[PDB]
Length: 266
Ligand SMILES: [Ca+2]
Image (cartoon, rainbow, N blue to C red; front, side, top):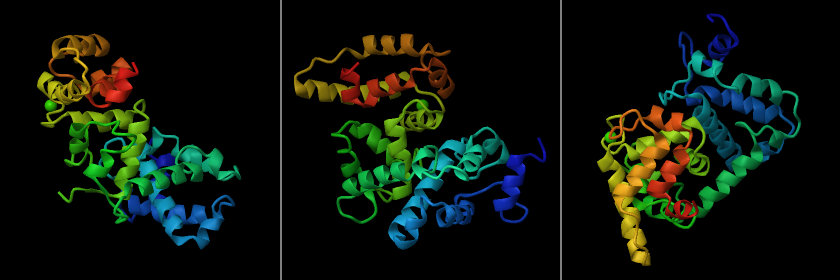
């Protein structure tokens, strides 16, 4: 609708005559939430955590709401999300950690500590090498190289904000942002489909791995058959994001190609 809650929300935070919101536009809203909410008022006295919390909540808002990945939230995007409802719930709930969408402090601190552990040089960036060791090398060097390629964002450095997107996507491959996130990493040539040679490229490292452990890996041919039966894409040699969301098993597909540990566990 033209004058709905989403539309009025946009007009409220947007710079004048703008129909969309950028990350910066949410800052005064977050500052207000942190200054007023009883669960968050300790943050006034911990400036590094004050800033990191706001950055993290904003990443989470965009992660879930900004489905076009444009960096600009529209009223349509808000209307299809639970953000305004979550604001309505925020105004009552006194335990910030019960607001598990967007705002949870506990969730933020989990993310912060994980970032802290990976930021080996303590320079506020994560290197490709360090990220490769996250979760005991759970991810392949080829998918990590793709993360650092610009596919989901060269300085060779992942910022705190971008780590938020990585972390959420690595832990939860069932939400649509994550599925797109891994799709963009697997879509090496960026043509919007996963071709069989893009699949082989990732699978051949898992093979180079398996072989190095003394495991004879299942031949590409049979695995690809499995994955096609799994996904049932419209076009076999051109798997789309739509095919992967529709099959409802995208996370299995993804593990099979770049999380060797979670694969063997299947
Ligand atoms: Ca492709």
